[PDB]
Length: 53
Image 1 (tube, rainbow, N blue to C red):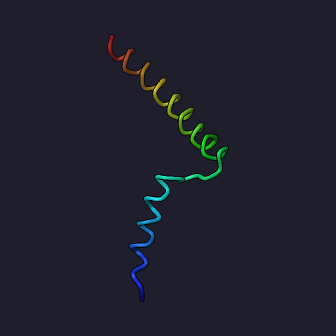
Image 2: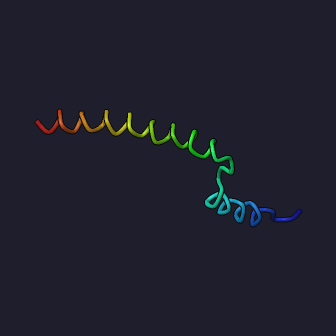
């Protein structure tokens, strides 16, 4: 029974490199994250401004 835990770890960091090789999926999926973050930040920002008053 080999560890294989170490390998997964090495591959885990590789992703930091090319977590998403596709030049489209890298931005499309990330776009959702970025866009998805804007919705969260915008909603959170109004809350703070509203609460600020």
